[PDB]
Amino acid sequence: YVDMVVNAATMMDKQNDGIELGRQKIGVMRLNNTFVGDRTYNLRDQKMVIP
Amino acid sequence: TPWSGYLDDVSAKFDTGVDNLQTQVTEALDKLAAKPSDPALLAAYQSKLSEYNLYRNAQSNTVKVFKDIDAAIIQNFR
Image 1 (tube, chains in turn brown, red):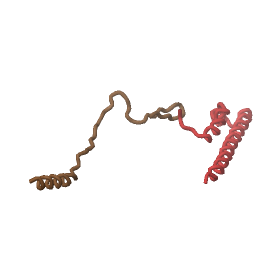
Image 2 (tube, helix red, strand yellow):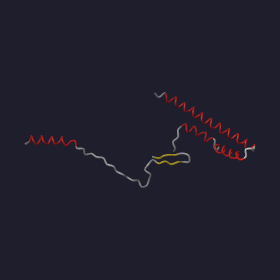
Image 3 (cartoon, rainbow over the protein chains, first blue to last red):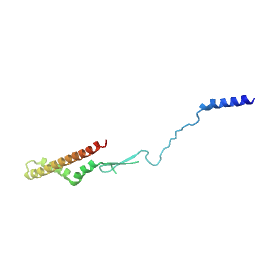
Image 4 (tube, rainbow over the protein chains, first blue to last red):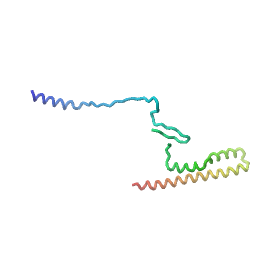
């Protein structure tokens, strides 16, 4: 009984080891009060840009 | 601020040195074209055109010389 139990358990353990459980997700977020992209202003003769 | 190199600065020195020549040289022509036979108009325009000519020449040759001084140094990094 003891030997069967220990063997079966140790085989089950290495068999299930390929299961992948860590996963990535995508979150969408709208800005309400500002422009999302890097922002250009044109001065009289020149563009200048803010991150 | 707007992005500008060192050649841009050397170039803009002239544009800010000649305060208004770029407009005067145009207006002088506009007047002259109205009555080509007026000698006073001709006399004025001659001097303005000549000054604009020399301004563009000096402006270009200087930029060229600083480009070469830079390239010579860059070449020696290796």
